[PDB]
Length: 418
Image 1 (cartoon, one colour):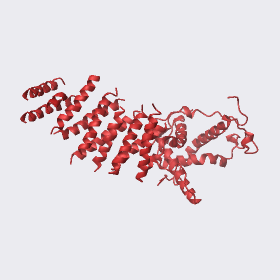
Image 2 (cartoon, one colour):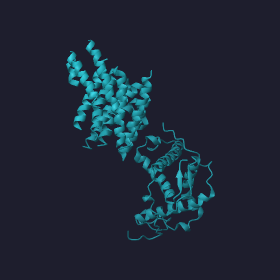
Image 3 (cartoon, helix red, strand yellow):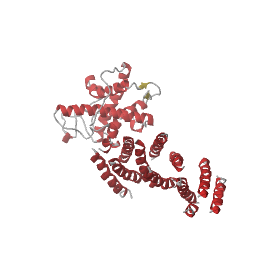
Image 4 (tube, one colour):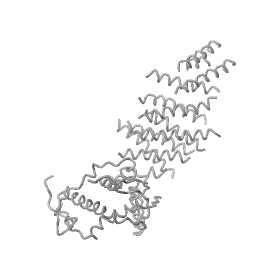
């Protein structure tokens, strides 16, 4: 429902969910990866844009929460019946469907099920536990037809599926298949995203047929009738096991199949891309939503592989965007809480910036004549130097020129920044 939100009372449900997620930090001191999908939905809420500031504060607590964890459905199913599968792939459908009966009979073997005259679940027996060879081809069609609708769903997406690489407990009564190990097959992240999108097909098609079915009965709805992006990853897993189901058998046959944590730090680099968009703002209402993302940055970094150190260099870049202001004010204070939090990014584990200190010293010459934001940036950078104490000297000699400016004379506190 949180991902369904991004009326406003569902964003308030995100606020109660945010403080309760901080109570989950107390339990902490998977489903959570789905909640990371819902954090990307929060970044979509940063894309969405006064009540917005409240729902942004609860979203800032949700950022504190996921950092502590790190320590109208409208289906549009693709065309299937339009598509025509080439005849040579149906011989492959004989293999994946024969495997479907081998695994569906073997699931029955996992609980000691056997062949019977009746569907008597007390008798520990089922009628269909007879060999896949014995099936009439129309009985094989009850297994094959969803598979054929899936291969047509891929060919409507025009995904390639083609020959390449070579293919590959006391015993139970009834037929006894020993299926090839699809579970040991591991899809590449390209093909894993392909499992994500075939699961998205199962979701939009079976979800649209489910919606029109319950409207055909005059009835209501089902829990899964929410958009596939909105789903928790555990709800996506059920369709995904059926997608990899496929795709894993496609990898085991060695067929080429194509469309034809660290990821949170990569999302932080997407937030740095939002900072590039904020430079586009700096060229001149969405930049205030970027300030919402700044509150989210101070809070998520207050809890704070190499992509993260790249995002530290991005801290130095958006610090240059502050340096444009050096020479709203509360968004800058959000950037200051984001600066101490950037010291915390220094705590997670170029020379150009020292040169900007030389500009900081010449600006100090203006002070000898007697705006101050380049001094305040220099004070937070001094706190970053205290972070260096936790762990370019000629620019320090330029700062010795600024010591000569100390000799030239509120200001003693800027001497304390030094």
